[PDB]
Amino acid sequence: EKGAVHRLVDTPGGRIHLVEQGTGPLVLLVHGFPESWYSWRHQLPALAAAGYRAAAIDVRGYGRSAKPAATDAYRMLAHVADNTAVVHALGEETATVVGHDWGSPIAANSALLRPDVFTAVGLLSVPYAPRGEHRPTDGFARIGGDEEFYVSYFQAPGRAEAEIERDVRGWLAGFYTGLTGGALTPEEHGRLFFVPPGAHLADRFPTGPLPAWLTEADLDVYSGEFERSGLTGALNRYRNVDRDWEDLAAWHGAPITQPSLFIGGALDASTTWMADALDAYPATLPGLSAAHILEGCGHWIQQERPDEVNRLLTQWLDGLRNSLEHHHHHH
Amino acid sequence: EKGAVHRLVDTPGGRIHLVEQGTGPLVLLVHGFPESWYSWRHQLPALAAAGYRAAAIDVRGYGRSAKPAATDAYRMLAHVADNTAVVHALGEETATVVGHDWGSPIAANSALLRPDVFTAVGLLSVPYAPRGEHRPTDGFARIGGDEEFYVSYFQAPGRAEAEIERDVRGWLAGFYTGLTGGALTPEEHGRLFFVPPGAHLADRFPTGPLPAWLTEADLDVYSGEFERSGLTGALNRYRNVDRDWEDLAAWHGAPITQPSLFIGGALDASTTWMADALDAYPATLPGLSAAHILEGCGHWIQQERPDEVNRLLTQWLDGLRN
Amino acid sequence: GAVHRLVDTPGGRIHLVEQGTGPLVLLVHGFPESWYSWRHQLPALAAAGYRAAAIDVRGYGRSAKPAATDAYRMLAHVADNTAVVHALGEETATVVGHDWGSPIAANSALLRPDVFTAVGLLSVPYAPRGEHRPTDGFARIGGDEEFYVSYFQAPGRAEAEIERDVRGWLAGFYTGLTGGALTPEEHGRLFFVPPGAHLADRFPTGPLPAWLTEADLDVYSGEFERSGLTGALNRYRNVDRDWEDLAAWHGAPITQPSLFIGGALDASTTWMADALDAYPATLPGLSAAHILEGCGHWIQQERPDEVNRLLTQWLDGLRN
Amino acid sequence: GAVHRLVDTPGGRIHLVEQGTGPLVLLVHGFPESWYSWRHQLPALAAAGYRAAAIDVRGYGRSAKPAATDAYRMLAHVADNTAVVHALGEETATVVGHDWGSPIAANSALLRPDVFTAVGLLSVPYAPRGEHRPTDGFARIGGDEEFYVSYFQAPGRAEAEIERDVRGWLAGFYTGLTGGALTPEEHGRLFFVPPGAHLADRFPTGPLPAWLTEADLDVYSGEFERSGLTGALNRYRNVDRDWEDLAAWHGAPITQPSLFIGGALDASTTWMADALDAYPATLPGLSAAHILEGCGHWIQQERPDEVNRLLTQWLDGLRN
Amino acid sequence: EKGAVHRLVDTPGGRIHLVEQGTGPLVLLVHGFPESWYSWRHQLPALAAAGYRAAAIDVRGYGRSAKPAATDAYRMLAHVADNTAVVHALGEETATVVGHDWGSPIAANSALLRPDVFTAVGLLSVPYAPRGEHRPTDGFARIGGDEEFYVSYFQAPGRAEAEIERDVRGWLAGFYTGLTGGALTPEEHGRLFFVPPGAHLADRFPTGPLPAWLTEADLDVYSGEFERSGLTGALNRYRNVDRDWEDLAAWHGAPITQPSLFIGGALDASTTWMADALDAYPATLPGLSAAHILEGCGHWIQQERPDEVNRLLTQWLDGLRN
Amino acid sequence: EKGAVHRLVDTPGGRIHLVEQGTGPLVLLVHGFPESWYSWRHQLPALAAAGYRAAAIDVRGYGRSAKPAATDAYRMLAHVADNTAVVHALGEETATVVGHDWGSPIAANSALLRPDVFTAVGLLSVPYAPRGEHRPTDGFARIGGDEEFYVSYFQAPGRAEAEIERDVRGWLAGFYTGLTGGALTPEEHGRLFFVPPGAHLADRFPTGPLPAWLTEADLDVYSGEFERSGLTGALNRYRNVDRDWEDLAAWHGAPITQPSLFIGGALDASTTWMADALDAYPATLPGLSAAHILEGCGHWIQQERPDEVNRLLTQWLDGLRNSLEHHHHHH
Ligand SMILES: C[As](C)(=O)[O-]
Ligand SMILES: C[As](C)(=O)[O-]
Ligand SMILES: C[As](C)(=O)[O-]
Ligand SMILES: C[As](C)(=O)[O-]
Ligand SMILES: C[As](C)(=O)[O-]
Ligand SMILES: C[As](C)(=O)[O-]
Ligand SMILES: [Cl-]
Ligand SMILES: [Cl-]
Ligand SMILES: [Cl-]
Ligand SMILES: [Cl-]
Ligand SMILES: [Cl-]
Ligand SMILES: [Cl-]
Ligand SMILES: [Cl-]
Ligand SMILES: [Cl-]
Ligand SMILES: [Cl-]
Ligand SMILES: [Cl-]
């Protein structure tokens, strides 16, 4: 908003747009799907006030950042190159990278592939899972039986786009609402991630009022982005899970040793469906400071619990600046 | 922005964004390349004050409107379907369509193919030329000599995009400035449209101050649209010239009989390079009220000469109403 | 008498056979037919005071057959008709189309009502452009079995079946859709292909129908043995493209005078009852909808005199 | 008299016109021609005691025209000829080919010498398969200008030129290669296309040649207005594939009795002098090589009686 | 190896590798899938001792022979051109061609298309069947039911490769073992050739000891070839069954008139699945000396029954020489 | 040969063949173009005798290693994953990687992307050049004017293969001979790397006797490999220079900090044409032990100077085990 400043920086893949606020060590924030730099609006002044230079990018394919045409231009190595060039373009040599949802694997792999640049890593909602042995799409395909796991539904180009483009604002509204903590029962919350043959993912989205974290003016911002960007850039992220599995094969099973932080929502499927990865943290994230679970919190962790995320981030950052268990938080 | 209202309407091709202002007969406004509904900001209050409902769309491929993946989804028949469905979605059965730059052939073919909907047509900068016998790319490739005509440069996917994406804001400012009336000499103006082999089109763009009609805040708006939309939807318009020439073959040499209006800039190549089209207006636009040439005006006619364009549109429109 | 002409068009060239003097009646044949399908109408129209011009549709006989599949989209057929009217020295015309020629004629009247000032539609009713993608509709019809229109979509698929014996395939198809040739049971299954089967596996065998002599079959088969069937089939392969191109006329009615003639034993008639029932709104200038008892698909050949009477009576009515 | 037949072949079907009784003489026309190019030979062969069968080559007239370009490779033409001999109830035949029919006949004799026991070659000499890729040779001929065979390689390119006016293009080509129609100067440039030009830009205009009446041109143009030119041109688009397929016969000679007839004013004759000079080794069973004075490319039509005499005299000689 | 000499000869399709031994009339040996010239190691000294020049090639796609990239470069006419040019490159005008497994149709069509070069033909394991009316893939797809016939499994590029590359040596050993006479019951033997959906062909391969004809050192040779060559050249042979059926249409139903010899294994599916082809030998191979069925012998006939195969070949060859 | 043992190991991209010899720390050797594991035959017993476990792989696309069909399966990240999986498959956690010619960028990038695995790196003939700003093929295209730089000549699939397949043994013989130290004058040596339009690269290869380092039996081994493998796998390496430039963008300008060693030949074009990269070593290889130039030595450094390479490698290794300038060596 105000105090925060928009920047356009050049990277090998092209233009990256970001909003930065504050002075001090660089904290690079990486949003998820289908989101925006604007998802960090609550973190930007808190990190700035706490003595940090926070920079929230638009991920490749999103908002005002470059959106290359080729699908493989959204492979993990491209996002990691995007982050590296942003740190350098901001005049820094190192940074803490914090990622949410798809920004979490982007942040983890940034820390994994360039540890001399990304010297600490925060992960929200999606735990770190090392590159594994099996092809992801063959895996997403076991799931569901009958119904198609939404990640498989997302693979075919133009398919999910056609569904979403029917009414972008409505589709975002349903998705934002549906994954908010407590918006759906566990049981419908789970059925939301599967698409019956011939159906649409949004057929199981709720239609009631916007959640408390999303005003109509906030939705105008989000829908205003995707009505302009389209969804292909965002969706191409999912369309590289196989390519990423090949590219990261040199880091098969590799741990992130740098200091790390995990914050997840108790009502977040991204957290509860990958509990095994989360429980492997003593081996996969040996430098983890702590794993925090926010009770009653859904998927949009840094907007559903902005003050709690702010508190945990800056406490963790400050601990690193002045130099295990699941910790569960109430409210 | 203050008076005008944003809307999203459904069309057979997907969502169309528009900004409308005023009450009365529908005047549909269609921007060109590389612009936005925002190019009509000075016309929306003027038409509204004159008793019209002005509706400025984002053309398919631009701003908040749908941007299909397929290059041929930007063929002329898609734009015309977009315009028709916009008139119907706004609750109207007829409308006047006014188009600038590429919006001009879009308005012309809207008037040509659906004369029962678009009952009068205004064309700015780009004259009406009926569908001809020659394949458009065969001509674009002929002129310029060793240098490549910019429309020909725009044909290959990703080529013009790669150039513009180097600096979307910078490219727009140069193009906006280069085509402003008097910003370049006529010689400099003419070669701006030709690309020497290995060169970039923007290599002949001027640098320095923005033209008077475009503030830095105006550039923030335009560049903010294209930093989100990309340039492919916009460029795909050029990539259908041969497809349109095929599609429009059933209206080969056909005139537009509706009442029509033409406004062009004396220093606009889009106007002065098609003098032959203007000379055929007595036959091709037999319902023409008048052809207006604005002396000293460049390409961005409704922003470079907003008051005279406003007056010409409303007086012409009122003329139809009596 | 009747005369062959080759006229220049934007897509290349249209071959046609014209007969008579007077207001121009452009005749547009269906699938898998020929200008020759109108042979009984050309002298009748000439005797009634009209200049009848029966084209070979793009892809057929002596007309241009471009290689690209989408060169057979509806807008191409319409430019073909427009250019033919102009090449014959006329400014307006009555267009009459049968089977696939019916939507070609209907869209000619719809897009250029200043040229096509009246329209005749045979066998296939007019349905305005709707919002559902045609191939999605053709899919989930049948189940299970593949609706023949879906069968026609894949390039080379129907061609490989027909080319086994162009003449035999033509005869079976002409025979199968003749009024009274099959039970309803047989008639309905003819339009569906079981997986791995051929469409013609359900074609009847035996004697040629009454409207088709052996010499008639020689003409038809002599054409397709030279042209092949791709141009004809590419017509079906543009239903989705057409649905996109015609979106600017979504739900639009045809307002100028129109005439419909269909067969009671024509599936094209009974499967599009809704379209026929919507005529008061979709064809408000409709003169009448005639359903000919016992008539199959090949209406202007199975009921040559009745079609001639209705057409010339309708035509005479317009200019009176 | 002469009779039309449709015979079944592995590639689909060959249409042909046969006349006479006796040993089978299969006639194979060139580009852009027809079975009809042999019209003066069919009665002559019948009167001399032979059953002459003039096919439409695959891609032409009423014969099958498969979609794939490589379905016009030389082995397909040879299976077509083999299947035709068998479909006509014969076990062996004499094959006589003109222009592109010459390599088709030559390779039929080469690959199935037990079926094709004698071979006639008109206009185009026999050259055994060599090791150089043909398209590489056609490239660096001319420079600078594009040899017409290279011009024929790209799909749609020659077709777009010809389809502007199939009849006019045919007439110009037939006229240009008629004996004496052009100066050497004009004749040589006809086979090269300057960049951006059309091959027919160097075709002569004016009266039809003496061998081609207006009614003759109606037949030819009536065929290609129905078939299009892709099947015919796909023949040229297989020179490289043929060069690969025929590698098992690299440098192989044709040993059974053979006959060559060429025109002195035929470029196909003068540009392949080396092939003609190598006949003692490449065609050791050669009866004679006849070069007809003043004759252009269309040898069996420009010199109908001389070709008839040489063929029947040669044929009578073999079985004596 | 000791007596035999390695050679590289030029052919129109590129380099062909072979190992030759002996002096006299040329006997060209053609291995099958997935083998090597090395499959003829027991025949090279025997033919040489009998007065013949035996030449065992690496088929195109195998070992040290050229392996073109294009799938259709493995069509039957390429193999025949390879064989012809090999005869000519070795300084001969004629030869006897003897082929095993896929080398059998290669030898048959070599004899069919160039009878002036290949004056007698031996066929092992795979009977001669003249080119028929039915598209080969239409048949392969019909049989097996819900399970997929292995030739049909081999059609898609990379599919069979991915399975085999999991463990080239292991796959070969299983296939070599599975088709050895008596290694499997006839029921197990038959389903080895069908792949249930989602399964791998090698899922039905036996494990355990190598067959008697193949030492570990022999497997090192075979696996060492395929670890370098890959399997695509070998599999591309199957990927041309429909192309060959088109290419060979000019020899539809044609018989091979040369003197011919057939040797097959009683427990070899390649032999027993084509009994109909064997029953037509009086018409299709009218120059057949005799059809030999080796009881208890499996697929790898010249290695499973080397002495009897050696005797049959040389006595047949000597029979031609008088 | 003997003492050395062949192994086949499984990697994410498939099978890697290698020959290993010795006991002690792992020294992974990576050959160049168009070579083989067999190029290290002289290093295998010397490293084994000096207390090291030397493992010479066949690079992806070569000899008995896997040769995937897709061209991009030869991107740098695949070679680096190949090396990582080989270290793990041999029961080790770290290794010294030593690469020659194309194995040198493979070894450097292995050390750059997985420094926790590859803890020291040796580079022969080809210096380390960080990922740069310009697209490689646009660069290879400036070169020559008229004549086509062989790297550009190598891009079109099937093009160089057709040339080489005309006579694989002859082509290797000419290339091996042509780049041997002192085999050609500087001037012809340079013209060898350019192809006039319509010509063949081998048209400028010498035809005399094999160089001293290559016996007829050695050439039988090399030609015996490529007559079986074909050249596409080897050439696809060159066909990924652009893809590599994208993939390594996250390491733009990045240095290798681990201990490094460079050995190059004085008569090696690979050394003299990239002198600028070699002279940037204080910044790009801050951990360089030394840069060694072997006088009179050509391209095939570890075969043209086997004892000198052995001596420099083991002295360097031993220095690391017990814990700037161009150094030029004579003979
Ligand atoms: C874990 As998600 C909602 O970005 O697919
Ligand atoms: C007609 As224009 C100069 O806007 O491309
Ligand atoms: C009703 As129909 C003969 O056009 O498929
Ligand atoms: C010599 As010709 C008519 O076949 O190009
Ligand atoms: C004929 As076979 C079993 O070797 O594919
Ligand atoms: C440096 As090199 C001979 O592998 O291209
Ligand atoms: Cl995109
Ligand atoms: Cl810090
Ligand atoms: Cl787009
Ligand atoms: Cl920028
Ligand atoms: Cl066609
Ligand atoms: Cl065709
Ligand atoms: Cl291969
Ligand atoms: Cl393995
Ligand atoms: Cl490969
Ligand atoms: Cl060490």
Image (cartoon, coloured by chain):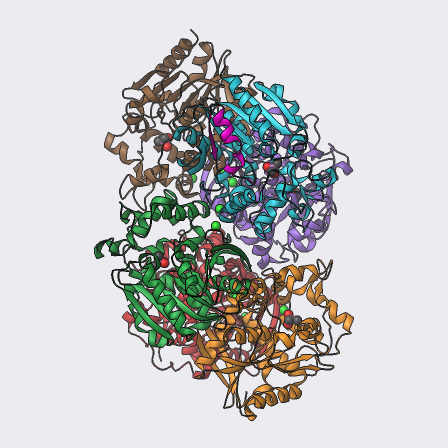
Chain colours: A red, B orange, C green, D cyan, E brown, F purple
Q: Give above or below for A279 relative to E20.
A: below
Q: Position of residue B166 (x, y in %)?
A: 64, 66
Tell me which segment is drawn in magenta: D32-55
How many badges with numbers are in the image? 0
Is D38 covered by the magenta stretch?
yes
Residue sitting nearer the eye, F69 or C204: C204
- Residue drawn at x 43%, y 28% is D85
Give x and y (percent) for residue C74.
Answer: 46, 63
Vertical placement of D118 versus B213: above or below? Answer: above
Query: Residue drawn 49% across and 41% down?
Result: D59
Q: Nearer the viewer, residue F36 or D178?
A: D178
Residue at x-position 42% and y-position 57%: C237
Q: In the rendered image, is residue E61 in sight?
A: no
Report if residue D287 lies within the magenta region: no
Quarter of the image for residue C319 reads bottom left
The quadrant of the image that shows the N terminus of chain B is bottom right
Residue nearest the viewer, comparing C31 with F166? C31
Q: Residue E286 lies in what quarter of the image?
A: top left
Quadrant of the drawing holding the C terminus of chain B: bottom right
- Frontmost residue, A313 versus C238: C238
Q: Quadrant of ligand 4?
A: top right
Depicted D213 relative to depicted A22: above or below? above
* Residue F93 appears in the picture as rendered: yes
Where does the image place residue C188, in percent across and percent down from the top left? 25, 57
Instruction: Give coordinates of residue D67: x percent, y percent.
Output: 47, 45
